[PDB]
Amino acid sequence: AQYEDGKQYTTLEKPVAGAPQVLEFFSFFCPHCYQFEEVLHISDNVKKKLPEGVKMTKYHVNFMGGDLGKDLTQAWAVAMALGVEDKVTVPLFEGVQKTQTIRSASDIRDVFINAGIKGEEYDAAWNSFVVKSLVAQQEKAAADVQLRGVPAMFVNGKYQLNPQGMDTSNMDVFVQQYADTVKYLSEK
């Protein structure tokens, strides 16, 4: 067929019940994730092609960057709680990987302040139990698919995108194949 298990996607041995419809995992430490987000704009091109009634979820992971990695998962929970993902994603990626000016929880916080989130508001969220449960959700989602690498995308808790089985000679064409594959899996 044109789409084949084991080629553009894989099937989870152990399907995950009640999983988000489209679930993407990343780390601000992850070099391919940087490419996916700032150069390829994967999350965005996927959404443009998702059928109506299909929601997209994006979670940060702990297993890269040690202590700072965990802080970033909590900051990403803060980002989700305040709904400011589209304001902090670029400066966090560049702060960790481009300028390398993010070295501590305080440096992460600076990114939010610079993005116009007020200090009291950031700190309140950071220390909130709503953010604690959002950290819990991120961890549990990754745990449910035995996640050992990023970037990763899962559709309906049963299919895992397989980008290594795609031509990367043209960046535009890779992105649409990725997006079209997600659309296909979504309609499965």
Image (cartoon, grey):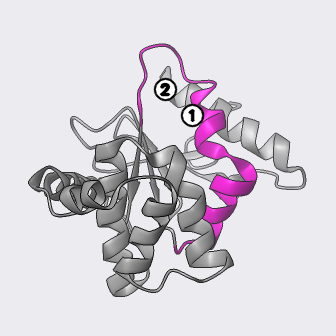
The structure residue drawn at horizontal position 44% and vertical position 60%, both measured from the top left corner, is: 112
Q: In the rendered view, does 172 fall on the left or right side of 81?
A: right
Which amino acid type is marked by label 1? Val
Q: Which mark is residue 186?
A: 2
Q: In the rendered view, does 8 fall on the left or right side of 130?
A: right
Query: Compared with residue 65, is residue 25 higher up or lower down, i.e. above or below?
Result: above
Q: Is residue 28 magenta?
A: no
Q: In the rendered view, does 27 fall on the left or right side of 127?
A: right
The magenta segment? 29-56
The structure residue drawn at horizontal position 22% and vertical position 55%, both measured from the top left corner, is: 125
Nearest the eye: 165 or 106: 106
Query: Compared with residue 163, is residue 56 higher up or lower down, i.e. above or below?
Result: above
The structure residue drawn at horizontal position 34% and vertical position 63%, both measured from the top left corner, is: 75
Pointer 1 residue: 182
Nearest the eye: 126 or 115: 115
Label 1 to label 2: alpha-carbon separation: 6 Å
Residue projecting furthest to the top: 52
Q: Which mark is residue 10?
A: none
**x, y percentage for residue 139?**
24, 61
Residue projecting furthest to the left: 129
Do callouts 1 and 2 mark residues in contact (Cβ within 8 Å)?
Answer: yes
Which amino acid type is marked by label 2? Ser
The structure residue drawn at horizontal position 37% and vertical position 79%, both measured from the top left corner, is: 106
Is there any visible trace of residue 101 in the rendered image? yes
Query: Compared with residue 66, is residue 128 higher up or lower down, i.e. above or below?
Result: above
Q: Is residue 35 magenta?
A: yes
